[PDB]
Length: 100
Image (tube, rainbow, N blue to C red; front, top):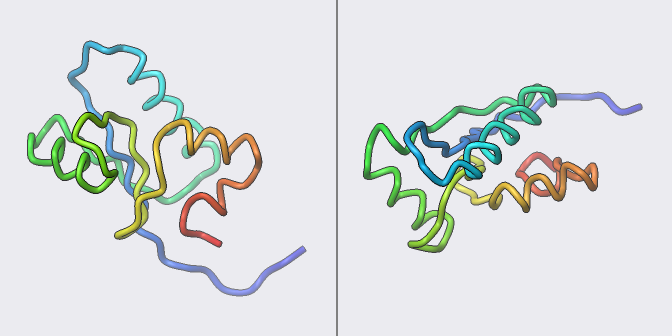
C-alpha cells in the first residue's frame, strides 16, 4: 500500500441545470456519479445560475463553443467528460486531474 499525508485540491464540476442538448446531462450526471462514487472532493459549479460562468468556463477550457460537464482543479483545466471518463476507465483519473 501507500499512506502519508493528504493534499488540498479545489475540484470544480462546471455543470448546468437548464439544457436541451440532453446528452450533456448524461455526461454531467455521470461525471458527478463517478466523482460521487470515487468520493472525490469537488464543487458543482452551476453555470446556468450565472451566465458569466457559461463564458468563464468556455475560456478556462479553451473554446467558446464549449459545453459541460467540465472538470477543473483549482486553477487548472482537467478536461471534458470524455477526457475524464477516459482516464477513469484507464484507472488514471488521479493522473488526469491534479492529484498526482
